[PDB]
Image (cartoon, coloured by chain):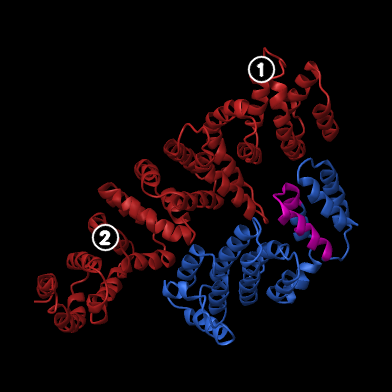
Amino acid sequence: XXXXXXXXXXXXXXXXXXXXXXXXXXXXXXXXXXXXXXXXXXXXXXXXXXXXXXXXXXXXXXXXXXXGXXXXXXXXXXXXXXXXXXXXXXXXXXXXXXXXXXXXXXXXXXXXXXXXXXXXXXXXXXXXXXXXXGXXXXXXXXXXXXXXXXXXXXXXXXXXXXXXXXXXXXXXXXXXXXXXXXXXXXXXXXXXXXXXXXXXXXXXXXXXXXXXXXXXX
Amino acid sequence: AVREAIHALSSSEDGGHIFCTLESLKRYXXXXXXXXXXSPVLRCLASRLSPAWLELXXXXXXXXPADQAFLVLMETIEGAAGPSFRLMKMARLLARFLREGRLAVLMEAQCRQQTQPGFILLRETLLGXXXXXXXXXXXXXXXXXXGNRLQQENLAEFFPQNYFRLLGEEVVRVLQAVVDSLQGGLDSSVSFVSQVLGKACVHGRQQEILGVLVPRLAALTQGSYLHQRVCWRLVEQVPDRAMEAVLTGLVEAALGPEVLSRLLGNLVVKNKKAQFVMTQKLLFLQSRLTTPMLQSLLGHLAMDSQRRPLLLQVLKELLETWGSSSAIRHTPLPQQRHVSKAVLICLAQLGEPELRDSRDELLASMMAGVKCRLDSSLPPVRRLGMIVAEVVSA
């Protein structure tokens, strides 16, 4: 409890982050580990840098490993899903940044790829603006980053995901999909279909289509 | 073809035209191509059904007025995506009057479609998705829907209790269906089940869970072995681990029924790993244990006998727990309660041999503990412990 509250020292500087790393890595790999951590963190989703910390604690201190990939996955997914399910301005933009960092630890550490990239296709799709891109590649752990770059099946998954839609998530998913230039080909045909849907859109699905169209261009 | 027809129907329609369009789904005769195509068609048609809501109150086909509503019930003879969109429009409100009727209908339709509901969950078991985290997200929302209806509240009607019952029945059905013999060997049975389970727990403890559980338990117990075990096993998540911790305790509160049946539930399954983890999680902590006294006891019994020596370790572990100093300074009085319970169980069973070695530790424990607790306000509480131990290795 103490620790949880504590993550907000007046004098953060470098010592602060050093110690952030310290506590996260102190968790290392004991009993309750991931689980315990996760619990408290999920409660006060105000500290995913601590999520990163412990993510990375597991990354350089552990056990149950694809199971830890799963734990990681869970937390990660959760984080994105909730957070990127709406919007923010001051604090939670940085929360998203922190989420990118925890994604990082996770991704790298686990080579998780399946869990990881379901959440990357998720989390990658998250990128959006500035910081986003940075975090994305970082978490990506280059091999898999380029793996995804190649990847087209994942792209199709995303295509239909977007088709179902929700909001801006879908919008920017399409944005970064485009960014991820390679060769549409199949995606070009898929996106033609998207457009068609796109075109159709009466509601905000209309602006979704606008951004989509930009991507297409 | 399909797309064209859909567009036409959505645009302009006379009575006969509308009728024919509706009958389109009935005719089908397009395998699953038609199905997926129409899944999208009906997504659009459900949006078109929001538009059809105003067309239904525009004196259209008075005779078969519920038919188009039955065409919405023909959607209700469809996919969970659509159920997906049922929830979507449910969120959507809009149709106030018409939607009240709609959702009323939706609800009882969906009592049947919750069967259908989790048969679509069972169909997902039969099927599979690589990017289905959102299927689960949707599923979660769908799970949430009983409480999301509550959330929606607004007018509100049949409640979550019944959601209770609904859930129970659904599960039952699923289970037996699955049972078949083993017409469903896929684990996705357990997946959906557990997904749901986890969700349930998260969503709500005590009443819901337990009621479901009780009925289920009884039935299941009575008639299942491999299958029983399987579902039980199937149980998952971390949220659901402690979800299951809680579940288990809910079931504990399920008392003696829980005891025998969860002697069989542990006999259905303990399967090492996470069980052990949460067993000790529980061991460590906590709140309320008259149920667990019994709880403790039976749980212990079950697991211990499932897999011997689990107990031993716990017993061994427990010795350490008896200590104080820092602990003497710390804690409240619940710890003591816990301690008492432990003592009792310990007394109950092991090997004999156990006594001897544990007595090494016991003696040790005793001594330090003695000092500490000799310092017990509840000097007698501590003394009682001593006597127990004393007895144990006279």
Residue A172 falls inside the magenta stretch? yes
Labelled disc at residue B296: 2
Q: Position of residue A116 (x, y in %)?
A: 65, 67
Q: Is residue B183 visible?
A: no
Neighbours of disc 1 within 10 Å: few (<14), some (14-19), many (20+) = some
State which quadrant residue B93 falls in: top right
> What residue would you read off at disc 1?
B65
Front-most of residues B380 and A86: A86
Q: Are marks 1 and 2 in contact (CB under 8 Å)?
A: no
Give above or below for B292 relative to B83.
Answer: below
State which quadrant residue B84 falls in: top right
Residue stretch in magenta:
A160-179
The quadrant of the image that shows the N terminus of chain B is top right
The prevailing secondary structure element of the residues shown in magenta is helix
Q: Colour of chain B?
A: red
Question: Is B251 left, or right, of B100 in this rendering?
Answer: left
From mark 1 to mark 2, how far is it between C-alphas?
Answer: 59 Å
| Labels 1, 2: front one | 1
State which quadrant residue A97 falls in: bottom right
Residue visible at 54% across and 81% down in the picture: A20
Question: Is A119 left, or right, of A20 in this rendering?
Answer: right
Neighbours of disc 2 within 10 Å: few (<14), some (14-19), many (20+) = many
Q: Position of residue B8 (x, y in %)?
A: 84, 28
